[PDB]
Image (tube, rainbow, N blue to C red; front, side, top):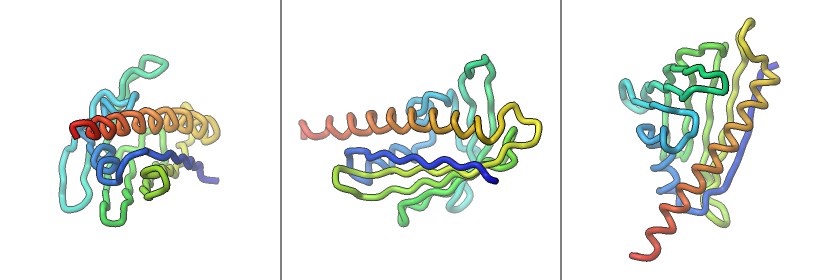
Length: 155
């Protein structure tokens, strides 16, 4: 009934670095290939609201929306959801980090459902999100590992 994506990847670096990089919202435009802009609108208490402005998609359209995000470094997890759902009836995000043999494993899970009349149906969006998510996790993994390996020669 409800759409879902579940993707994992291991980053060959320590939790601290993996966490700090991925949770650096201001840097997402250089980390993610889809976001042109990312700014925190407000930070009240734990969670916070941020705006995302994507780059022109495969159809030349630029999207922008606001989401609420609540990072929990202590539990090594983060929860988020779109405030301006747009074509989505709702979109929930859940990231976890786990120490494993070789580095830090990142697991990103999405829970959503398209609005009746949206350009995409649950099936097609699921495929689209898996593709973009996998591409982003691989790019982020590379970036983090490079920063990590750099600090091993100064040391």
